[PDB]
Amino acid sequence: EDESEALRQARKDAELTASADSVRAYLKQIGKVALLNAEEEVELAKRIEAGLYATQLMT
DNA sequence: AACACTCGTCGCCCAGAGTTCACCTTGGAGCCAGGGACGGTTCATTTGGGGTGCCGGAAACGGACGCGTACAGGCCGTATAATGGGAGCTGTCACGGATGCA
Picture 1: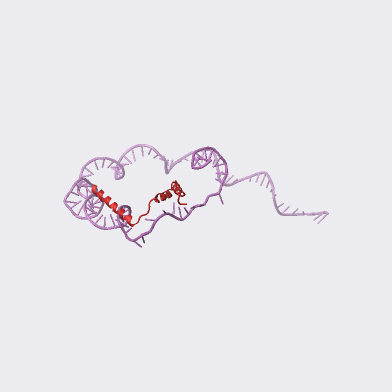
Picture 2: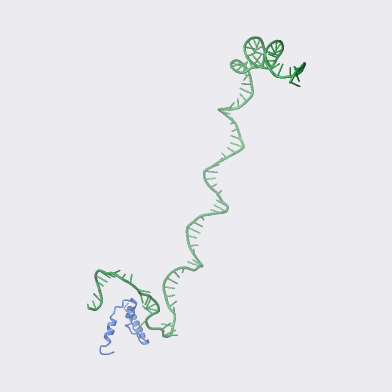
């Protein structure tokens, strides 16, 4: 079923697939990153603002 | 069936058709001689006329020259939330060989 090495190897072998169609391959590759929410996006904005400010300072 | 009359045909004889043969004239046909005027030529004028190169300049005219306007195309931004495609139709066969699995 779910545990005892039952379907994890199936998921791994599924992810290790050619997927010769480029659109399907792109969808597979885009599938590996989780969605965000309001909090995560706002602190990401804080981080990029800090990076831009530091880059301007070094310039 | 018996009986007593008038008409082509030819020759011949004399005069001219018109034709030839053969005689005198006279208007020549042209041949040349002489004299214009004449039209073709040439050369004097004769100033009536064509002519002109350039310009003051007046006006067109061709274009430059500077400066406005005009859409065409390009860049740019829109703050609720909106977080993984439809569709494709696929009856071949031969068959050599690689090829992903045996």
